[PDB]
Length: 106
Length: 107
Length: 107
Length: 106
Ligand SMILES: OC[C@@]1(O)CC[C@@H]([C@@H]2CC[C@](O)(CO)CO2)OC1
Image 1 (cartoon, protein in one colour):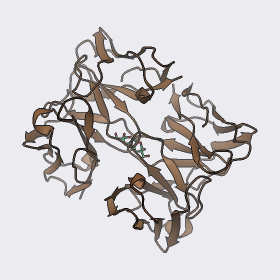
Image 2 (spheres, chains in turn blue, yellow, purple, red):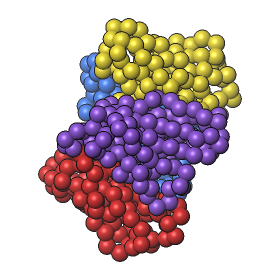
Image 3 (tube, each protein chain N blue to C red):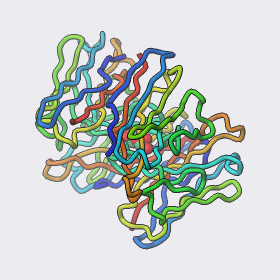
Image 4 (spheres, chains in turn green, red, cyan, brown):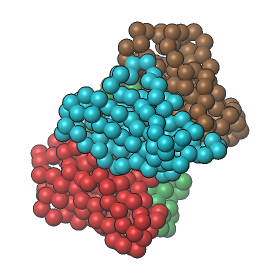
């Protein structure tokens, strides 16, 4: 299980940082996706720091020991969504998730 | 939905299901696949066309062919009943595109 | 899904679409209907079989026949393209049941 | 539209209160539903205070002036979800929503 804050809120154009923590993160890749009702999930970062095509450069990913972090610079209204981190247990046998973080733009 | 995906695919347990998405930009743009079950976080099952994240069973596999990508689920089990989504980017690689989702019914 | 609902219904603009859910407990249990568009909050469009919350257009209407309930959308507009969900309760009225959702495609 | 806190978190068995504010609420009904990925929305309260069949008694709704409130007594793990209030503008012409509140059970 991964620990993630329930919500992060920032005013427009601020940077938001969303961190997940977990014992297995030092040895397991994380994936970050954006969840909105009614549409496919949108992968914003894979393997800790890689960005899929079509994803704005303002989205970036980093990792440090038992944490991984999605940073969103210059937050826009369309960024309002839930962000989930996905990884795997220490053994790499099964998928593990954070509880999701709701990003609000004040 | 700029990717064309059938709304429904059904198979009995043990069969292999193939879920396809179609789009003009798929040849030179990676696809990503998700599984969505009721009341659970979505799961990334394939990225970059064919790679599985740690923890994803090998019975899930992705492939690319012309203007179509395919999620193939071998030996479908009851618990695989879920919605499956595909994501990619447009021909330029400037914005994300996605299919409407396929409901996989088992039985 | 203890209610059964077609995964897909399609009509051209201006037509009337009928989306149906079926279940043994529907006769003596109210149904509720939602509209889900991409990237937006779900919308309650019908409650108690046939009542429309304030702000829902009269072109959306709900009805109830035997073991089926029906969301009828008259004068379908392109912006009505969405997923539609039905919810009710079991026979006794002890827990909630749902359909798998219908994708309405507007041609 | 409507103002709702981004998130509410309580330990198991506590009571959670989720409030929506809006100028038109004194004259317009509110509806509360539970949103989870992958499933139909679940209406827990309609017309301010009425509960659909199949909804546990621990869910209740109240209204007071420019506010409406969903109260969840004895919060349980399956209650973890987003809760949205829906209403209508002052004229009753168009639908309005809160931004959703993510309920976390610590
Ligand atoms: O109102 C229906 C939904 O609850 C279905 C799923 C949920 C989203 C919609 C589809 C989803 O994003 C696909 O991963 C999963 O969660 O929002 C709306």
